[PDB]
Length: 247
Ligand SMILES: C[C@](O)(COc1c(F)c(F)c(F)c(F)c1F)C(=O)Nc1ccc([N+](=O)[O-])c(C(F)(F)F)c1
Image (cartoon, rainbow, N blue to C red):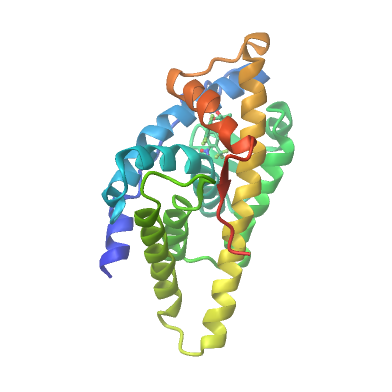
């Protein structure tokens, strides 16, 4: 189980937001903590991605672009799984010190997106998603959103993606003889994977609008994040960069 050994080994540890939970909730404070957390997380996502089997096959410029475009979806997926395993989807577990209840969901002005993410979180339970299916699916999300014009080396990307889809096949094929059971499983998962994109899209839009009026809402945006939102996210919202759906 070489492939799974590796994913397990590189899976990031706990990342805290540094939020002050002794202070009443406020839009500004919550979003400032979400931005800070996002920035702390990106550092880990980058290190994780670069340690993924075959990732260095990609062109240097494609590596970062791919990481920045898929960043949101990866987090959404992981956060959903964390919510599932930690609080049984009761609340959104962004971090041990940044857990959202309905009040915070409403206060953050990200209610609709939070509700979709909670539903995703419940999906891991309804579908009895295994810890290993989760790891492979999350890896697959890194190769699920590219520019319409293609990357420097599209072919190496396509190869990479194809090989990851196959590993997911393998984790499903294991302990499964009847093809009809595997085909049904593959359907549910690819179907689950597709659902992540629309959620990331909504967060992107929310994040973009917020950055534009940040100076009006007293919301602090970290250096790196701001750059990605202003340079990368617009490409996604304008359609130049799009996700790869299964269905
Ligand atoms: C509002 C923002 O701070 C924006 O930061 C991000 C951003 F600007 C991006 F372009 C991203 F791709 C991204 F993943 C961000 F978090 C945010 O969505 N933060 C955030 C922090 C943690 C998590 N998390 O732990 O999964 C999430 C998420 F993914 F929505 F749930 C968002």
